[PDB]
Length: 457
Image 1: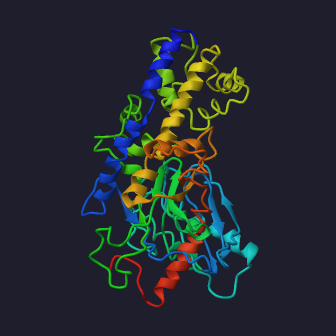
Image 2: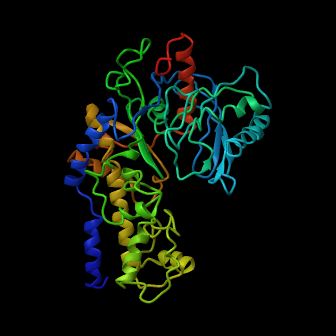
């Protein structure tokens, strides 16, 4: 705004500004890291989605899904029919308090009721004995599905007295009140490899963009180092290892983690999830707030004001991106948002320090995002492809052309559009309740011809 200011901005365009060279030394270590578990050990997660088959697109039947985390749980049944899906859902809001609880006894004691008021309303019973699938975006330590045991608590969630098969757990309430079959407990990260691989033949990935960023790509059972149990496993071809790049580079020897990047941690549940705490959709709005805070003290802006805004993480993700979506420009929506929130008033020189941060914060978290979709696709050498990318983060101020345009950075693609663009990140088909239906539809299948489904009994 004001040269003086115009200098304070400068420097966080340094902080919060992420380039190729950075991106590319990050992409080249992401390999290591990526190849690292697969092996015997590894600081970066890597659990299959335990999906050994390859959606045939002509697969068909009745299934179920549900997507649990966020604030709402959904239900959907479907009928595949020649590369086409036909689900029906909804669900109910993480009924206020769903963090601190304990128990599938309360948290697990509702997804039913929930399923309850479903059925009875659509089918009003059913003739066959329906099958099912239910995703765990929390702690994945997948060894099958019907499996799904906790690896490490998370998602931003809390229904404690969980951290155990916080998964195969639900089920039990299934039979308890009952009526069905939980065939799999997965991740949504693949339901985009899988369900959209169904829908889209050239689909190379399953990457998702939220509170947690992540992705999943198909290795070849001979890439994995899970290869000490097989038999009926194609012996080398098709296998959807569940990535979980959330845990990417905390040995911290490579992510450009700036200086606020260090905060969120210490003050937070600490020293956790580096590549998402620095690439994520849900922790960013707050970053705003560590910076805005720091300039509040060397007294750069809010020239006098009241900070009740200092609530140690008092504001979210929608905020900083609304500052960005900021329609007019003189930035009056920002003027609103703050007033009556923490109600501050600073000058368009202020809304201009704020709208800028909110930028880099974006461009680097997105730009920084896709510095993955490439480390993999290189590790596996894809030349071309698509990527079903999915996450609210993808309905966030100017962002899809970063991941995208940003990829060309790592890569270097000198072409017309993304479209025209050598590797294109396209939106994926329903990955949390869809990948679901079709991930099960393959599960069952594989079973019969008593083929195989987990790490050898």
